[PDB]
Image 1 (cartoon, rainbow over the protein chains, first blue to last red):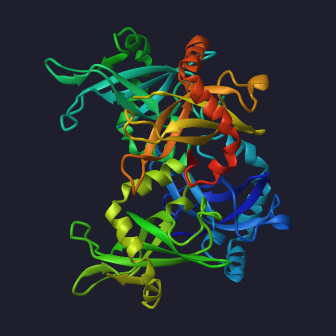
Image 2: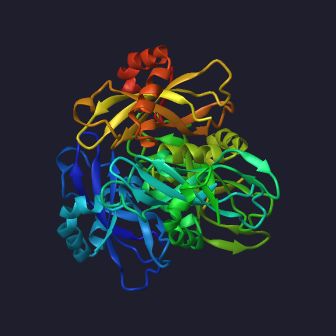
Image 3: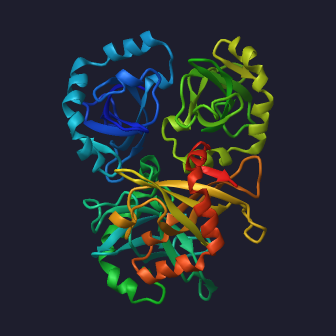
Length: 129
Length: 127
Length: 127
Length: 129
């Protein structure tokens, strides 16, 4: 219902950071997934300060909300990722979350961090792979 | 009142949006569909690639003059892009999905009526 | 389903929000008012000064387990801050104003029932 | 109905600018005004590039939307300013707008540009004077 997605710091600025998440745009989650990259500008994530406030830092997340596509039904045209660290202070539950997310989803996200500007060129900060 | 709008023309230093609006003052009646146009310069989020004829722009129908003859209807309605208030992607995406797909289709099919709309007194043409 | 929530406790590395929720499954009935709490760490926009007991946080009531005895009601309801989806100021301000002032007042008056709520099975206490 | 407010560039960054506007938080505009500062992060304003993309540049604006206060009625607790340059390409209508806004409102705004960080410390980017 609120399942885990990988997210990662894609850019770091003085006042905020940009996180990119790997999300499934299918409304029906049982189908083969339709992967996309979703970005979000974030000011603060507990635990992410200083030496971990770096491009490439892993952030376990969930897709908290989305909006349906007009032309399609069956697809989300917008998806908001949130770090699970906003919901729990517990380091081991966050650590668990990270290991639970498939390594291959982690690697897919890592390989696409460099597409940040392509993603930000879309109208809802969502770019289908 | 949420309405679909769409970029109908793009020029070097301005653009024109067209909206599909209901001119009846009584919203409980079957809609009295009309096309309304507005010359604008910029919309937050509408940059380069997405700045083209056909791009969807959710809007609100700002009503003006009303009069009563054979119908009680608005004589002027001006679309205001929602992104003028906030370009938040959840807001704009939700607004687009809240507008019935039939209205988006109707607007896109009438997009070529721009010159006819601009020939009316208030840039408003009942369909 | 939009509900008022409020910071009920602030700790070094976490905080607790309380929401005023309706536990009836049938929304056409007079509400069955309850208080629901959730331990969270952070909310976009809730930083330093505004991070204190009493701060208003508009939320949605995420429903869980339902069962039918003398009433058909939700056994679990968890508030989710709207700012988790987007901290856009128009969104958060509109959501706060959309929730009746009577509900905000009721929540603020019951804010001191935190320990009683946390003593229930699902952090949900019918009023 | 959509009346003119002064706005001014309060901060300039690589990807965007922050504009501050002087707004009236009274829902009833006939009353003596209840002045406040409202800020907004803006990516692009026609005409504002390069030498005019500077802290202190005047931007004629209107208060396009607002949200009511919960405890009060009679007050807006959030107000979105927009540059009139988003609505018209015509340099003289924008120039007119600027001269139409009272000089004293201009000066009040100029004198408070330095309160940017106070305004951004509020929950809806609105600080009553």
